[PDB]
Image (tube, rainbow, N blue to C red; front, side, top):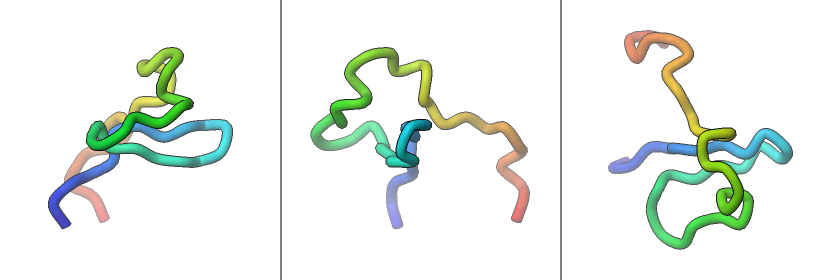
Length: 44
């Protein structure tokens, strides 16, 4: 494992990571579906 998700579509649950060919759902407003640290990165 060497990469991590960056975006997640709220309509279908699909994900992307800022690498390779960009998704079709990405091509409208990137800020709407970005993944964010809603909880600390020190949790399991």
